[PDB]
Length: 121
Length: 267
Ligand SMILES: Nc1nc2c(ncn2[C@@H]2O[C@@H]3COP(=O)(O)O[C@H]4[C@@H](O)[C@H](n5cnc6c(=O)[nH]c(N)nc65)O[C@@H]4COP(=O)(O)O[C@H]3[C@H]2O)c(=O)[nH]1
Ligand SMILES: Nc1nc2c(ncn2[C@@H]2O[C@@H]3COP(=O)(O)O[C@H]4[C@@H](O)[C@H](n5cnc6c(=O)[nH]c(N)nc65)O[C@@H]4COP(=O)(O)O[C@H]3[C@H]2O)c(=O)[nH]1
Image 1 (cartoon, each protein chain N blue to C red):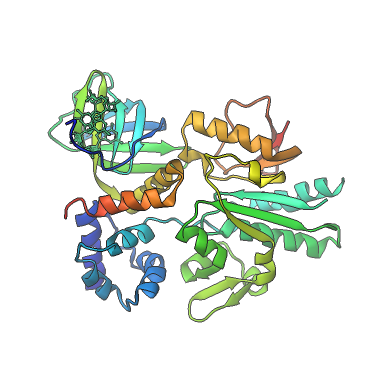
Image 2 (cartoon, rainbow over the protein chains, first blue to last red):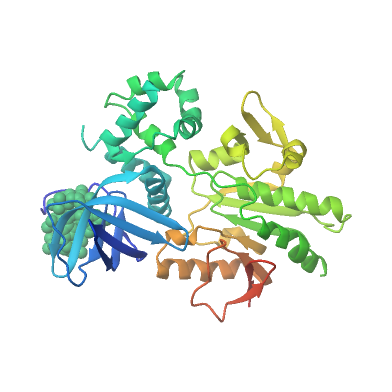
């Protein structure tokens, strides 16, 4: 909704990415990432159940993998927006490194972490 | 441990972070600094203090928990290449300037300083003029700990031979070691946004930029690599991560075969 304020900064990103659900797997084109979600292109044969969780795998180079449980937030005109739900410590540590390096200011990262830890206050 | 299990609950409930039940050791290491400054004497007290919800303590905990530290002498072979090929190549020619980009907790620039010292001890005063290592990252607590040069048991328990530990570190009480001041003096730490201009950095014989460009898009990392090329003296070398290739810059960089691994010569 247009009156809402985005909590986290979205970063244009293009790492090799997949979406998983059950036994299903889709290669997807990544568009952006944030500390709390991703934007991907809708793949072929998209029968992903929108009411059930998905998993995203972002391949950073050859030997770094960011894994996150995601929920479908919105879908339209060939795009899929996902919200991060659960993420392992190593994956969020890589994600935090990505976000801080692309923000270029550690204090902007701290404000993002402040919004993340207080989201369910 | 009950306190540790409650901490796992905190991380999941607040941020959705899933902490394995096998990471008590990692929690203690990453929160040691913060608990010291905060006057907190146990994880259990930390868990009590973080229920709430006001203040910036919860952010500081998540901050410390999500910072990765780098490894000592990461991959081994780039430092052998440095001592066996690059430094002899440069001596056949002047103060040495090395850029350690995105130095994180400092393990790489201090590893470079130790490798330089090992070369200088086995090779005369062949490095007549001296060596300067410029180590850069974003300002904050991680770069601040790099400057301090102090490391805990977890950081010291891997990648460092007992020969190097005795030769290059000072014990600083239980479970802490500091890089020896002579080794630290070679390194100068600076705050630098890799997305900003490198004009203030001067020129380098060598750039180490390892396992960092994976955090940038294809277009952004190409621009960083192009501007890194501007900081290299002619014929200088760029070191990437062991699994990193340099994409779409054939006129600027020439791959050079090492034994094993590769480095990139600035054309
Ligand atoms: N349900 C949902 N849909 C999303 C979200 N993000 C993006 N979209 C969809 O993607 C379209 C384009 O987003 P945009 O490129 O960021 O470009 C957007 C964006 O830049 C801006 N905008 C609109 N609303 C907001 C907002 O609440 N916050 C911010 N920071 N920008 C907004 O206006 C442009 C067009 O907005 P739209 O017409 O709404 O069309 C949006 C919207 O349909 C989201 O978090 N939730
Ligand atoms: N990296 C990334 N993450 C994404 C993207 N889209 C959604 N998310 C994540 O999913 C969360 C929920 O989106 P929402 O439920 O639609 O609810 C959204 C949405 O309703 C509204 N909103 C924000 N931006 C737009 C927009 O451009 N268009 C529209 N129609 N709504 C927007 O604000 C709410 C909160 O936005 P957020 O705080 O950002 O929180 C977003 C965001 O963290 C994306 O394209 N990239």
